[PDB]
Amino acid sequence: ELPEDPRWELPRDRLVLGKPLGQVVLAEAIGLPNRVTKVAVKMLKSDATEKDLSDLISEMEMMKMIGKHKNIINLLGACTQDGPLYVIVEYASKGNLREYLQARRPPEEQLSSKDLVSCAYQVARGMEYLASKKCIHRDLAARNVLVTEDNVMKIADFGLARDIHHIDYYKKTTNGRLPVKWMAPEALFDRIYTHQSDVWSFGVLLWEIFTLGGSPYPGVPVEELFKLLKEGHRMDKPSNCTNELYMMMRDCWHAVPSQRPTFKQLVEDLDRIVALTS
Amino acid sequence: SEYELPEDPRWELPRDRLVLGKPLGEGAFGQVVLAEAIGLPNRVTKVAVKMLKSDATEKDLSDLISEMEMMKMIGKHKNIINLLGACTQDGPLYVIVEYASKGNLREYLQARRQLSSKDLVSCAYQVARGMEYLASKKCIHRDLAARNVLVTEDNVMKIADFGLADYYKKGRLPVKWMAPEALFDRIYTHQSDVWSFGVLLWEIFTLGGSPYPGVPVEELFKLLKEGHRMDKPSNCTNELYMMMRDCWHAVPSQRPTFKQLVEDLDRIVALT
Image 1 (cartoon, rainbow over the protein chains, first blue to last red):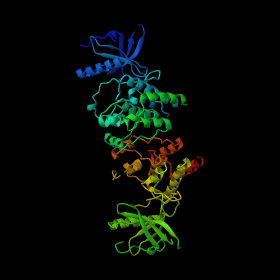
Image 2: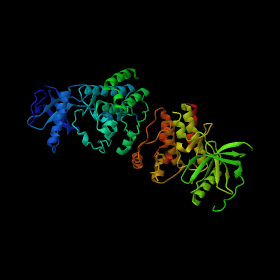
Image 3: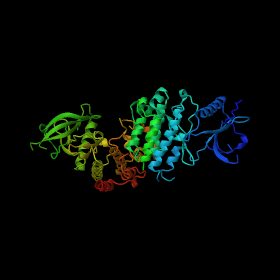
Image 4: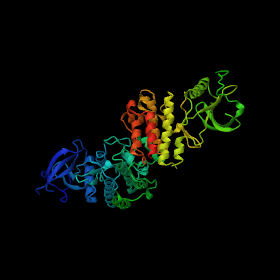
């Protein structure tokens, strides 16, 4: 059924499947000849539909088109013949960014201010590459940034298939948060997604970094969030965050999409700030 | 109180010695107007006059009288709105209190978003002192918030509505200042006031910030149960934040007393 692609195919016997990561399982790839590499393997569930199959294929195809970058979860290979489709991608042993930040809050080693700004920089770089490749994430948040054993930030789920005109606004994340809290007003209210709306989301992610995994608008339900947005509300400055970095967040949250900085600009600014950060 | 109220020579002021002025505020069935009092002996003092609205009932009268009497029992203090007199005979009851030209603390703070770090800590010290006094006088405020702290022309903080006789009545929600036991176990104590003071401290350091914006009552209840605490404001020392966190201790007996808070705030103001 699936078309062969010599560019990415890995023999099934080269993939030693292991512990479920989240369907995604950790595995060891032999070769990719006598070396194993820990990798993450994406596959469908037993009750997956043909639509589910198509979405997994689309994501893999999208990853192929987009190409590689140090700050995104990269495609490593695939098992598409005679068996379940396996989409092999990079493994991030330290989990998502939200978790990573929370685990390092003071009463695991505390992150320095430079560490925090560097985290933001890497994310902005991953996004800068994605935007250059014509990709709009649509759900940029710390939950969607994974951290490798070497502390490299990698944007995940950038090629995910999603029907925006079918998003359940009242649906929560696994951690119990509302994804609508990362959406630009034009994406939320008008269903218009752009690189500009991704920048707004990046502003929220910046906030998450400086609050060390903080939850935006705690206790605020969908309906109330709509009202806050309509009224032009902006979250307060996290303590232990410079006015400069807060200004950046506020610029990312400009009501006018055309007035927000681009990821290219953000990368340059963050590059500047990191170097100047203690 | 239908035909005449009891007389108290000690506080009575002749109506001719009081010229009513512009209204300062309307409430449920109460009205407050600015006025000029003469000889509280030929000098005029700008004062605030609390009276009933034309639609008030006997119960409302009882409530205004109970408040005046409480003010009498409590006595005077620099950081509370003090009773200056009353017109109880031959006409509407007027409870004359100190006037605070700079409005409530919330508005005072926002209008100056310019106070120094010492000014902000000083504000908290003054409020805690007013409260330490009220607490020494057995008075439990039950709604201590920046909105209930008035500021005089000389920038003196004065606790208001401490003698006053629906979780969804706002456009902020007062339940957001309530201690858990007071909100859940309807238990009001001097320590529940301490929790409220912590939220007031937060208001001071955010310069009139709105606690829990967009958070409805039901959601607050959930946040409270989860042990959720508001984040440390920017431009707030970890010490002052720990004080807030202290005031927000789940066990009321573990929260500091206003006497402690006054001592600490006295110390911090100096080191600021």
